[PDB]
Image: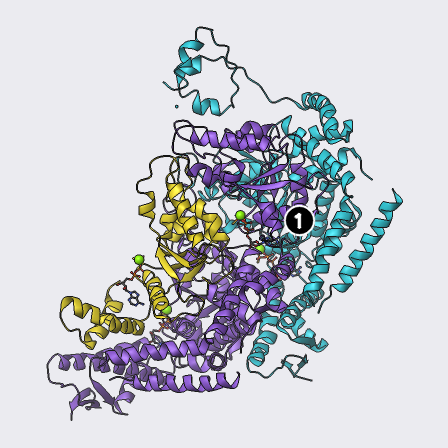
Chain colours: A yellow, B purple, C cyan
Amino acid sequence: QVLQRRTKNNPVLIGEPGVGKTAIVEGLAQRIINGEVPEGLKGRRVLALDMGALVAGAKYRGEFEERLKGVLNDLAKQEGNVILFIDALHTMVGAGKADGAMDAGNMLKPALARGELHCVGATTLDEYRQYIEKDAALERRFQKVFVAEPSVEDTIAILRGLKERYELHHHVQITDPAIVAAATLSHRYIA
Amino acid sequence: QALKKYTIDLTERAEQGKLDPVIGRDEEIRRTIQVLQRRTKNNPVLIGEPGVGKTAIVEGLAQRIINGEVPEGLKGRRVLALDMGALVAGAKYRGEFEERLKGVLNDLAKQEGNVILFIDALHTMVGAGKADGAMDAGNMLKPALARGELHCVGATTLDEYRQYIEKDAALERRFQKVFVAEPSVEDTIAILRGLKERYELHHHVQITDPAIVAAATLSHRYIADRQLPDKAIDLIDEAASSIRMQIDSKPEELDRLDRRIIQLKLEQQALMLDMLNEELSDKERQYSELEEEWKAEKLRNKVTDAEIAEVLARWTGIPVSRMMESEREKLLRMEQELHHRVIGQNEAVDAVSNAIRRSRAGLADPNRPIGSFLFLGPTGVGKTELCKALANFMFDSDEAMVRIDMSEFMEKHSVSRLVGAPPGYVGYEEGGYLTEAVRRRPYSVILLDAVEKAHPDVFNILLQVLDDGRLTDGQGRTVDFRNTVVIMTSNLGSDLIQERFGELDYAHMKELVLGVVSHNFRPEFINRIDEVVVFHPLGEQHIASIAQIQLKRLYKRLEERGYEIHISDEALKLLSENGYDPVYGARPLKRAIQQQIENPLAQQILSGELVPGKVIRLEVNEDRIVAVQH
Amino acid sequence: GMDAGNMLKPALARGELHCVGATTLDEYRQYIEKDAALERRFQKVFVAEPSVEDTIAILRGLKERYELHHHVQITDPAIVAAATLSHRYIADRQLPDKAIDLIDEAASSIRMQIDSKPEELDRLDRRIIQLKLEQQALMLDMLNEELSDKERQYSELEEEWKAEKLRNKVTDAEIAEVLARWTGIPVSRMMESEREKLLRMEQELHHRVIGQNEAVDAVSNAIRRSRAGLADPNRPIGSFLFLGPTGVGKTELCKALANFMFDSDEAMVRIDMSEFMEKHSVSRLVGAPPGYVGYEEGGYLTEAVRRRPYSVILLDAVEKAHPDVFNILLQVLDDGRLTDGQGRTVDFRNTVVIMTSNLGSDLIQERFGELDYAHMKELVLGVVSHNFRPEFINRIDEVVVFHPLGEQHIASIAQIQLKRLYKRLEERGYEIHISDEALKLLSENGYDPVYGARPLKRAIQQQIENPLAQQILSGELVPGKVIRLEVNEDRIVAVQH
Ligand SMILES: Nc1ncnc2c1ncn2[C@@H]1O[C@H](COP(=O)(O)OP(=O)(O)OP(O)(O)=S)[C@@H](O)[C@H]1O
Ligand SMILES: Nc1ncnc2c1ncn2[C@@H]1O[C@H](COP(=O)(O)OP(=O)(O)OP(O)(O)=S)[C@@H](O)[C@H]1O
Ligand SMILES: Nc1ncnc2c1ncn2[C@@H]1O[C@H](COP(=O)(O)OP(=O)(O)OP(O)(O)=S)[C@@H](O)[C@H]1O
Ligand SMILES: Nc1ncnc2c1ncn2[C@@H]1O[C@H](COP(=O)(O)OP(=O)(O)OP(O)(O)=S)[C@@H](O)[C@H]1O
Ligand SMILES: [Mg+2]
Ligand SMILES: [Mg+2]
Ligand SMILES: [Mg+2]
Ligand SMILES: [Mg+2]
């Protein structure tokens, strides 16, 4: 619902660490593949923008800015087809900030407001406080989707779903009492 | 040229109909025009909080220039938006950036003064391109800004301005601070009534004018991080997206039930005891009923104020939505659902219930918290049980509540541990405990347990909190407490209540114990309290009912282990008569259950004597409770 | 780019190069005093900020120049007013620069009013086209009356503009208007609407603060001293201390000021002084000193006043704090200045400082009868003398004493709170008339002198809003009928007739 707005198509996924925030965007990408989204998103491309690969080899004045501007022009060339994904959005906040350099916050800050960049974020609820609420303009560019920690029954359903992958990796069999024991006991004892 | 490569002509985009309508802001656009037509320092900076309409004022200036709604000096000007990112973006070599910026200034000089330059994020000019050849792009525009040969309209923020522009006071004089205020509720209603048509034509919905006035009002009340008109437009836009997605595939409840039946389909695949085929059968039946009803009504295609209430309930967290029939029937059985865990104690369960019915009916005072109670009475009577029953009713978890134990707060420093340290000190950036927690989830239940065990002037923080719903942490931001329920459990009249609960009605008891509380508290603080409710000690029928509650949760603690336990109707009489004394409430019942059942029962489970599967009956001896195997 | 300083550094201490530099007083410290050899190549000529009369001379020559640019006339009283008003109210910048800024923006405003049309015609033109598009959007209203009134007034001012066919000079009034829009302080002359509002100051405060006459008078007199140009320009506008028992309307009078002056209750620098029960909460309100954690974020009071210099500063329940905060207030209240941790002084001279407290609660509740106002003020001021220092209660402009609320007062407050309850239920979609016997039950089940007028709010809350919320949620009461709050023998009950 937030990605298909007119302006500010920017959902930042915010929860504690471990609650399944990268997994929500992976589930979104799998629903776009399987066709389980509405007709508006049928055929979108979830691209994962890399802050480390943009900052990496750019030591001259105006090389990060040129890489990032080429990224923005290629996304504008796609005619609104690419859902952009930035996890650890606070890394985007302080990315290309050299001595008098246009960092990634201040260069994405016009296109995020104008709804022409469909940036899905993901940041922890305390990285958000340290880093993103520090800068209130880029903070208002994004809409917060609070990802709550799931219950024990939800965790049993998750583990029943991920069971086959751990069986195919470890070459063992995981029994359903082990699943309800893992969810119950780790919810009770691990703090 | 150089202006065509590093600017974007806003009057062309206003001419082509690509900028939004700009509504109101008459004073601000007028003062921008008065500062642009000076002789020296032609430079207005638009300065306000983020979201209040600063870029909107410059786009409105471009649209009045196109429509000829300006004075005769401006008819024919061009508004070019300087993009500082491109200027820095290509400029790899020494002198390349300075050449680009000087070429921009020469082409601006060749326009005979017929260009309004625009630099939003004006603070990205102090230090743009500083290097070994530190010409910095603020130091190069500074002669042209000094002499009024450049009509630069800047638009920085209000904190960005201080951190970036006021550090350099030679450029800070070159501009003219045009302060842009946040629009009121009425002005935002007038804004949304003109921007309505563009969001309608993008989302292919109709936005009813009650949804506009409701969006402005509800975002002004229930959102505190953001500012009008931005959050009102957020509610309108996301509700239109929601309606468009419903019309696109299928409505809400059909999506909920379809996802949960495919969920339980995968989970029933994973279970190949269950109590799942019952759940999947119920959800399939309800999905087929709603599919029949959806084929009967063949809905939501408009955007009313109910959609705005749903979007605000998912954004913030506060339930402002309309009460659906299941939740409304749940909330009329508020008192009945709370006596499944707090037996006895009618007055406080009613008081809690009336506060949440005021809050959901839409009758609560918007300037105070939802309910600010003071629980009093002896020990073990269901004070903290009623607070945990509240949190379990309201959030479907017992410890889903901001709980503050006021017995860690015996000294006057704990004020700092709940609002955080001031600037300069150790826990400055770590925030405060109460402020951060309520600012995360604004709609919450706050418990302040054992309130007499604190220093007496710790509750002055709560004077602010309970009267106005506001509390400012050390960093200077005020947290809003107007959607919280603040509960303060205490026992300041326990000897009096145990002494005279006989031969007195409830009102005389409240009068006398409230005099005792006046001896302990201040007249400011027991005036902020919504309702003081006084608890009563537990009689024998109460401890019989509490014994049934605690034995039910013991049966659940041992059924999950794999043991089925019945009890005699006489052994429950022994627990109810051994665990009764009118001074300690319902804890002697709990350690009597603990001893007289769980010590022999755990003695025998570890012994291997009691095989699972067989029904473990708890029958009496002459004085004991023995477990048998038959 | 050695690069550009070490190249010239031999060529400067031999006199061959005649380099006249011109740098700022802080760019020299940052960039030239860092390198001591280049620092001794130059002779520091000190260009000090001129006085007001030097600024008047500068503006006379520049009057000639800016008149020949804007094609207006600048009157010499506008020059002496630009120098005086910019020296007093603009604390951000310096002379003669900000005086030239007032002169040039006033000439721009006069040129635009000559060019298109006057101010009030543009105001009403934009408002009638705005409400015309809003009526087009409303195609309940209560807007046709307002738009018809604005169209009538625009037709009247258009006829008067044809009757005088204005402003073509630049006098001191336009200088004051440019200053009032630069800063925010109403330095402007009083128009008819603002002055008719401001002589109704005490009437417009008693629509929200019933009772409490002396405090309304003191507040009203402070703001009428301010607008008439009679305030002491070295102190703040007013600096009060509100005393009384609880629930008598202290924080209400502060909110009624903010709503009067600023159109909102939440437009005030509200400082909850009970958070300052330590000795380092001074650093909460002034700021961290250099080299510390919260340094870059400024203070709280200093930033809030330095954004908006004309404001209302509430210091709520001020007796709760620790007395060092009152030392910070000594600076603020005497000379209208406060230096924050970054070393920049903030001009508090256009603010109203209000300090609510309840230091004589028992004394006012015990002896407000059989004493006049003066002896009551004397006795509670003795109590204040015990709590505060003779420094601090010597800078207080006026110590007003609030009285406990009587039966007629709580009846009037009951009508105010029932009007806002009618507002909530009307915005929900319901209508309530109340019975006069029910209003007697409210005004009699909510009267006790020790707690003021919050027991009234609790009695309204319980005896109306708990059964009314029980009935609205039950489906029992229907949108579109008058809910008569009638009485049983002891209870207010709601019906549907
Ligand atoms: N709903 C889910 N369904 C299936 N697997 C999940 C789900 N949520 C989380 N997981 C798994 O849980 C693990 C961690 O979840 P992540 O989303 O990667 O953590 P995170 O939310 O990214 O938090 P951080 O900030 O990255 S530590 C991974 O193995 C995920 O596959
Ligand atoms: N007065 C107004 N009339 C019409 N639309 C407005 C008005 N003010 C704001 N808006 C719209 O509301 C949103 C506010 O966004 P912006 O004004 O661009 O934010 P901003 O004012 O630039 O503040 P920052 O610091 O740049 S994020 C945009 O969609 C604007 O088009
Ligand atoms: N009215 C009650 N209904 C049900 N269980 C109760 C009731 N009163 C006490 N209990 C049980 O007794 C235990 C202790 O009661 P609490 O309510 O926690 O005591 P308390 O009311 O907090 O009094 P203090 O002064 O805090 S010790 C709870 O965990 C419940 O299991
Ligand atoms: N004169 C009054 N007119 C109208 N409402 C009033 C009046 N006095 C008090 N009230 C109401 O009482 C509430 C609290 O009054 P306040 O003045 O805020 O209390 P207070 O003066 O701060 O005294 P303390 O220190 O809190 S006990 C307000 O929210 C009003 O609704
Ligand atoms: Mg992750
Ligand atoms: Mg902007
Ligand atoms: Mg307890
Ligand atoms: Mg108060």
Front residue (pair B69, B535): B69
Q: Which residue is mark 1?
A: C400
User: At which x and y percent is residue C412?
Assistant: 70, 65
For badge 1, the amino acid type reads Val
Residue lying farthest to the right in this orientation: C163
Taking A190 as reference, is B527 left or right? Answer: right
Taking B313 as reference, is B574 left or right? Answer: left
Q: Residue at x 49, y 48 (%)?
A: A110
Q: Residue at x 58, y 74 (%)?
A: C462
- In the rendered view, tell whether residue C24 sits above or below residue C201: above
Residue B295 in sight here: yes
The answer to which image quadrant residue C491 occupies is: bottom right
- In the rendered view, tell whether residue C19 sits above or below residue B238: above
- In the rendered view, tell whether residue B384 sits above or below residue B226: below
The answer to which image quadrant residue B367 occupies is: bottom right
Q: Is mark 1 within 8 Å of ligand 4?
A: no
User: At which x and y percent is residue B572?
Assistant: 28, 88
Residue lying farthest to the front in this orientation: B1
Front residue (pair A180, A108): A108
Taking B102 as reference, is B391 left or right? Answer: left
